[PDB]
Image 1 (cartoon, rainbow over the protein chains, first blue to last red):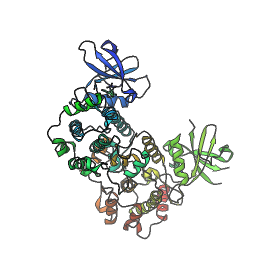
Image 2 (cartoon, chains in turn brown, orange; image 1 turned 45 degrees about the horizontal axis):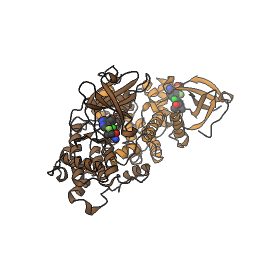
Image 3 (cartoon, rainbow over the protein chains, first blue to last red; image 1 turned 60 degrees about the vertical axis):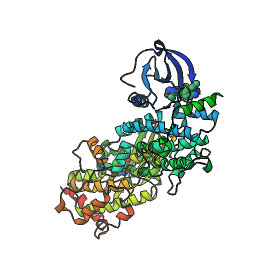
Image 4 (cartoon, rainbow over the protein chains, first blue to last red; image 1 turned 90 degrees about the horizontal axis):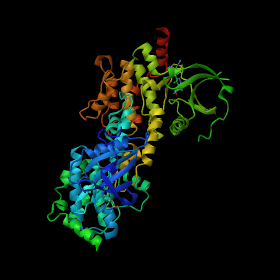
Length: 291
Length: 285
Ligand SMILES: CN(C)C(=O)c1c(N)ccc(-c2cnc3c(c2Cl)[C@@]2(CC[C@@H](O)C2)CN3)c1F
Ligand SMILES: CN(C)C(=O)c1c(N)ccc(-c2cnc3c(c2Cl)[C@@]2(CC[C@@H](O)C2)CN3)c1F
């Protein structure tokens, strides 16, 4: 089955569907209003026909329902009704940061610092649970109408958890296989510090409206990262950003994962521990979006 | 598609004699050209992984890798024609004869390393070196076999790459796992170390421990590579060969070509006559 706690009932008995959200980038997502509280939620609808694979969807719900942290999108349960799965989540009324900067242009360094602190808080919590987001980017950082920051979309993370379970289920007899082969089969070949690198790239994304090498063919970018002399990217405009921001980029984009700072360590960095970082900075951004 | 497929009736060319392998390697027949003997593996045509397996065997041309002769397509059945190894696998052998002598193990290890060094310079990985996949012919000569696991891993690596998504936010270690899999050909060197213990003791180390427990242990970093059970039975050279092939760190594990310079497999007197002696034991015991 997909999850042992699924509500086997029509979601429309609890929510009035209001409008579609996200333009389809996140699937079929509906804005909905609770019929008793009046609170707003987002409902993602996924098809669940009898003989489809449920493993990835199962992993995604398992990840969502065991998170209870302010900087992670809240989970309110799922509804299975007539071969449709509705995932009920916290509604973030300003969309993703990508939705926002595609209108406003590049974020200020202080706005990027607040965002980075809030994501690091969410990442420290996930890493403390032995979870890995693995798809940190502007599109998966959501903003509510109060200017707060919420990590969302564990679909990639669920995809990898499902691979891990399958490859482990059919790994076969292990008495002859090398330790490093067993470790890739059980652990995946990397660890939660990949999230720290992705935040570094996301910080550049917010500063420059594209990740580095966005205009390079994706298979070429993958190949360049595997070469011995590969150089981590940097911010484009040196004089636009303080040395603190430049250093933040340098350390998050540490090439060797053995030397890359963890999320708790990054929270002590000058850029995200400076005073004056609060949701008002993003309300300013939302006001610019509005004006 | 394989451009060399023979689109004709294989029984128009071979007499099908007995089955072989007890079904462990699939449906494979001992065949006689209709005086040469071949092995014919048949598979029902429902297949990209089967494609990839044949390409591995077809492109390999080395005396220590089981030879490939061609494939016939007929009545939705694919007939893969290969070199026949009349003494079966080393597992078939030692289950009758008992543990191999150190000299016999040394010769088998040299022959397998020769095949591995060829494979690794072809940018291939066997990934299932074990007694069951090391075959012996009637001359006592050693041939690596069964690239099915190698084909499946290469297909999983290719497919998971085709659904990896945009890579601009990916860390370089994640990129490396996507393109290269997370390990390399030195895993075959470790598997050979285990195999040599298998040939000496009739079982790989930890054979009587639950497999999911053995997977749990191998990833703990406190993990200690196994050793030969009975010290006084084997020379210091054998023990050292086990030590170096079972190097935990893949960054320090010697390559196949380097291992060919090890004392155990470079000593004189290593030849097929040792396995002819073994093949005499299975006949006379
Ligand atoms: C008018 N607005 C704001 C939108 O159309 C809009 C938008 N452009 C972008 C993103 C969201 C949004 C808000 N909250 C969410 C979600 C999303 Cl996608 C999810 C996370 C991903 C998916 O699982 C559903 C859960 N909570 C939008 F509503
Ligand atoms: C009476 N004997 C000896 C056997 O039954 C016997 C046996 N017990 C074990 C192995 C073989 C054997 C010999 N030569 C082979 C093959 C195998 Cl399986 C393959 C290698 C890969 C596989 O796909 C087909 C091609 N060359 C046996 F014939």
